[PDB]
Amino acid sequence: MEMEKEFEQIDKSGSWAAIYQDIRHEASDFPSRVAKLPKNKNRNRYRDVSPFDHSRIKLHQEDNDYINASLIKMEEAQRSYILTQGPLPNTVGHFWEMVWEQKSRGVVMLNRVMEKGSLKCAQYWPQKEEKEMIFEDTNLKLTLISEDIKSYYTVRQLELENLTTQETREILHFHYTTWPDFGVPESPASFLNFLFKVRESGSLSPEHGPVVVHCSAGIGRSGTFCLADTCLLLMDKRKDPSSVDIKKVLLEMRKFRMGLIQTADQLRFSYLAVIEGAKFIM
Ligand SMILES: O=C1O[C@H]2CN[C@@H]3CC[C@H]([C@H]2C3)N1Cc1ccccc1
Image (cartoon, rainbow, N blue to C red; front, top):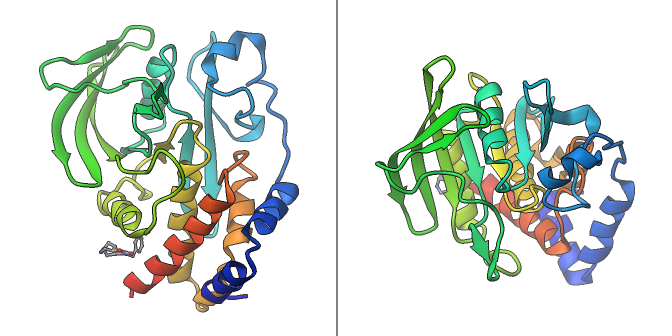
């Protein structure tokens, strides 16, 4: 079926939970043996969210190459994404090592450091120009260059230096700051505006490594971001945009990381975002 009228048909019939449970039942199951090794316990935020072995990002280190991060490679859309958990106190150096080694231009953050009165990720970037951060375990330096605070999101320019080679690179930090502590946004308008700002920066384009996108677990809000982006790109590429099937795209993405889209409300919000976005594109 088309999307907008399939949408109204699920609303009128109140069957979002049944649709979402079908997706959970059909989703791929692949091994995640490296994630579960005892030496990696303090590298995982949640015991039930792990990268598959076949798609995990490897650190360029011989001691321990493990990070909780996955490469989502979308063949028809010609887009790739790295989805990862919010960094932990003992993985902030690994996180920036990955950004460096994978040649990423942009980092997309969809959570606040504290939500619901608890810490959802480490403070992993500097908040003042004159107070830079050094990660001694991976030999990197990170400096805040500029910050632009808007009503729904903040964009930061950062300098990442590999202290071993003295090479430097400019990284863009796109921080969506207004996702509610509970539920999903009422309108997709600010989320879509944010997606378009990430696109306009070049961070999603083939001349760079894959964008790094995270929330707390790296599957819910993060899944909504890449699902909406890929569906909108396919609607622009194909002769028949009504052929784009958001459930099929989501199942394709779940071949590369488990659990993408965590609730039926996130699934409905993803439909809403793609529907409204397709009208603005034209
Ligand atoms: O829904 C939108 O809100 C607009 C505000 N105005 C800009 C033009 C594109 C717009 C957004 C930025 N879109 C559609 C869209 C959004 C993301 C990706 C692909 C298409």
